Protein backbone atom coordinates (compact mmCIF):
# COMPACT_ATOMS: atom_id res chain seq x y z
CA UNK A 1 0.00 0.00 0.00
CA UNK A 2 2.13 2.87 -1.25
CA UNK A 3 0.23 6.11 -0.90
CA UNK A 4 -0.20 8.86 -3.44
CA UNK A 5 0.58 12.02 -1.47
CA UNK A 6 -1.46 15.08 -2.36
CA UNK A 7 -0.07 18.64 -2.07
CA UNK A 8 -1.66 19.01 1.39
CA UNK A 9 -0.06 15.89 2.86
CA UNK A 10 -3.34 14.00 2.63
CA UNK A 11 -2.39 10.64 1.13
CA UNK A 12 -4.47 7.80 -0.24
CA UNK A 13 -4.45 4.36 -1.77
CA UNK A 14 -7.50 2.91 -3.53
CA UNK A 15 -7.34 -0.71 -2.43
CA UNK A 16 -10.56 -1.46 -4.31
CA UNK A 17 -11.92 1.00 -6.86
CA UNK A 18 -15.66 1.58 -6.58
CA UNK A 19 -18.06 0.23 -9.19
CA UNK A 20 -20.56 3.07 -8.84
CA UNK A 21 -20.80 6.93 -8.96
CA UNK A 22 -18.37 9.34 -7.33
CA UNK A 23 -19.35 10.98 -4.05
CA UNK A 24 -21.12 14.34 -4.26
CA UNK A 25 -20.95 17.26 -1.82
CA UNK A 26 -23.89 17.57 0.55
CA UNK A 27 -24.94 13.94 0.09
CA UNK A 28 -25.85 11.80 3.12
CA UNK A 29 -23.73 8.66 2.75
CA UNK A 30 -22.93 5.40 4.54
CA UNK A 31 -19.43 4.30 5.41
CA UNK A 32 -17.81 1.55 7.42
CA UNK A 33 -14.33 2.30 8.69
CA UNK A 34 -11.46 1.41 10.98
CA UNK A 35 -9.26 4.20 12.31
CA UNK A 36 -5.74 3.44 13.57
CA UNK A 37 -2.77 5.42 14.88
CA UNK A 38 0.61 4.83 13.18
CA UNK A 39 1.56 2.23 15.78
CA UNK A 40 -1.36 0.07 14.70
CA UNK A 41 -3.66 0.87 17.62
CA UNK A 42 -7.30 1.03 16.55
CA UNK A 43 -8.91 4.11 18.12
CA UNK A 44 -12.36 3.80 16.55
CA UNK A 45 -14.35 1.76 14.07
CA UNK A 46 -17.85 1.50 12.69
CA UNK A 47 -17.63 -2.22 13.49
CA UNK A 48 -17.04 -1.55 17.19
CA UNK A 49 -20.04 0.77 17.14
CA UNK A 50 -22.10 -1.96 15.48
CA UNK A 51 -23.27 0.22 12.60
CA UNK A 52 -22.06 2.23 9.58
CA UNK A 53 -21.47 5.92 10.05
CA UNK A 54 -24.09 7.80 8.06
CA UNK A 55 -23.23 11.44 7.62
CA UNK A 56 -23.28 14.33 5.16
CA UNK A 57 -20.03 14.57 3.15
CA UNK A 58 -18.19 17.78 2.26
CA UNK A 59 -19.95 20.07 4.72
CA UNK A 60 -17.69 19.91 7.78
CA UNK A 61 -19.53 17.14 9.62
CA UNK A 62 -16.30 15.10 9.85
CA UNK A 63 -12.59 15.98 9.92
CA UNK A 64 -11.28 17.80 6.83
CA UNK A 65 -9.25 14.74 5.84
CA UNK A 66 -12.45 12.75 5.44
CA UNK A 67 -14.23 15.42 3.39
CA UNK A 68 -11.21 15.87 1.13
CA UNK A 69 -10.23 12.20 1.17
CA UNK A 70 -13.70 11.00 0.13
CA UNK A 71 -14.97 13.85 -2.06
CA UNK A 72 -11.53 14.52 -3.46
CA UNK A 73 -9.36 17.61 -3.61
CA UNK A 74 -6.27 18.89 -5.43
CA UNK A 75 -4.27 15.71 -6.03
CA UNK A 76 -7.06 13.47 -4.71
CA UNK A 77 -9.71 11.81 -6.93
CA UNK A 78 -13.12 11.14 -5.38
CA UNK A 79 -14.00 7.73 -3.98
CA UNK A 80 -16.58 5.82 -5.98
CA UNK A 81 -19.59 3.99 -4.58
CA UNK A 82 -18.49 0.58 -3.32
CA UNK A 83 -14.84 1.46 -3.04
CA UNK A 84 -12.33 0.70 -0.31
CA UNK A 85 -9.73 3.35 0.36
CA UNK A 86 -6.93 3.83 2.85
CA UNK A 87 -6.25 7.41 3.91
CA UNK A 88 -3.23 8.85 5.68
CA UNK A 89 -4.27 12.10 7.32
CA UNK A 90 -1.81 14.65 8.76
CA UNK A 91 -2.89 16.25 12.10
CA UNK A 92 -3.69 19.57 10.43
CA UNK A 93 -6.53 17.84 8.53
CA UNK A 94 -7.61 15.82 11.56
CA UNK A 95 -7.51 16.77 15.27
CA UNK A 96 -4.35 18.89 15.24
CA UNK A 97 -2.52 19.79 18.45
CA UNK A 98 -5.67 19.29 20.54
CA UNK A 99 -6.12 15.57 19.91
CA UNK A 100 -9.42 13.79 20.52
CA UNK A 101 -11.12 11.60 23.13
CA UNK A 102 -9.28 13.38 25.91
CA UNK A 103 -9.24 12.94 29.66
CA UNK A 104 -7.21 15.89 30.83
CA UNK A 105 -4.07 15.89 28.74
CA UNK A 106 -4.33 12.18 27.93
CA UNK A 107 -6.16 11.47 24.66
CA UNK A 108 -7.26 8.36 22.78
CA UNK A 109 -5.93 10.31 19.79
CA UNK A 110 -2.74 12.09 20.92
CA UNK A 111 -2.03 15.66 19.87
CA UNK A 112 -0.35 15.94 16.46
CA UNK A 113 -1.42 12.42 15.47
CA UNK A 114 -1.29 11.25 11.86
CA UNK A 115 -4.44 9.17 11.33
CA UNK A 116 -4.88 6.06 9.19
CA UNK A 117 -8.37 5.11 8.04
CA UNK A 118 -9.59 2.19 5.98
CA UNK A 119 -12.84 3.48 4.50
CA UNK A 120 -15.57 1.47 2.83
CA UNK A 121 -17.84 3.86 0.93
CA UNK A 122 -21.04 1.78 0.84
CA UNK A 123 -23.11 4.38 -0.95
CA UNK A 124 -25.75 7.01 -0.28
CA UNK A 125 -27.93 6.74 2.82
Image (spheres, rainbow, N blue to C red):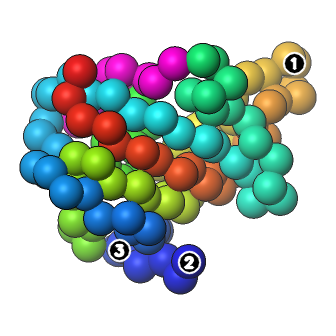
Disc 2 target residue: 1
Q: Quadrant of the C terminus?
A: top left
Q: Residues within 10 Å of mark 2 (few under 14, many from 20)?
A: few
Question: Taking 50 as reference, is 110 left or right?
Answer: right
Q: Which residues are magenta?
A: 51-61
| Disc 3, SS | loop
Q: Is residue 40 visible?
A: yes
Residue 57: % across, % down:
26, 32
Residue positioned 26% across, 72% down in the render: 75
Q: Earlier in the sequence, mark 1 or mark 2?
A: 2
Q: Earlier in the sequence, mark 1 or mark 3?
A: 3
Report if the CB atoms under discs 3 and 2 are less than 8 Å apart: no
Q: Tell me if residue 94 comes above or below residue 8 in the rendering.
A: above
Residue 52 falls inside the magenta stretch: yes
Q: Quadrant of residue 106?
A: top right
Residue positioned 80% across, 31% down in the render: 108
| Disc 2, SS | loop
Residue 16: % across, % down:
38, 64
Amino acid sequence: CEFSVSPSGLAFCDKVVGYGPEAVKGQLIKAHYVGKLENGKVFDSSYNRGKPLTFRIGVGEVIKGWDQGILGSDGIPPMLTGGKRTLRIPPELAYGDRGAGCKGGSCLIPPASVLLFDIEYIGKA
